Length: 57
Length: 357
Image (cartoon, rainbow over the protein chains, first blue to last red):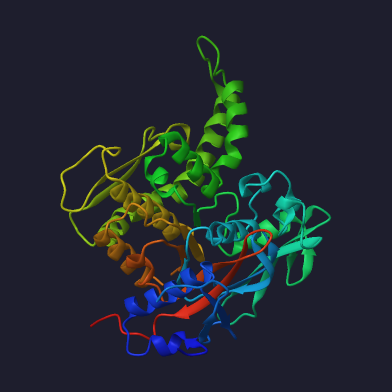
């Protein structure tokens, strides 16, 4: 796997409902501490890195 | 104008200083349970003048992050709203907790609550009527309220209620309360004159709302068979008794009102909310989980109404992707681990993606 995941890259060639679901999944994964999240500015890319708890898939 | 952004510092779970937004014309706040969405609703209420009793705390200082566990993160906290209008510089309205009491500011100049409220009123933000804010679990009650409580809303917005005390005094001076009232001459004319003043103030507002509500209920319902009727129980003195609200759902036979579904009541409530706006426009609405009882058909019709109107801005909190995927942008709330709940936000632009296949 990779060192980081770009939400905007994940959402390339997705439709609005699919993109929103990926955004929401980042919020859930962060709550579960499966990822850390950074966003440089409002509406910039959102970057996930591995969080302090293990997670499947 | 419109709400460009909210800035929050150490308010409830919003630790540190955070920008909320910027907002688009239709923005949805979303996030997993427990993340802090309801605290963000509280922050908006707070900067728009809500009393501390309605913010789920016993004392103002308990709104500072960490205070409900004896570990306050600061001796101050604030919420601020940046209000924007075409051709005008941004105006910042802030409420700061200092010394355990509220300090109000407009463009960083300290004002008293009276002036803060007066300036908000000039923008269409009525911090007494609070017709721009719908809390979770409350949208249906708007359509199913007591007729008498509906009258009180109209007396507040129309300012006819400012005349009720003089009305009551003149009514008694004219003989109301006697076995056989004998009104004549100047005492009777004094009562008729204040009655007329109260009637005129009330109807300037009410008649406008009642004559616009049917089209809005239709426009919401997207159906000419829907009908909405607002009428006073007392036509001669509308402010004295209840305001009846009855609807006919689109493509349905008439049912009383309590027999409507939660979704149908929700749409009736929204029609009244937006009919009030047609008379006294608010710059934005904050709608907390108003889609809870709506099916997917009604979610689409409500979202379409918002998008084909955004004369107002809509800020919604939603648990339903069918609704929030119709917004222009999402503000996502997530929790951080700590001594107490810490909330932070992300922003996401949905307009970059086709809403199609």
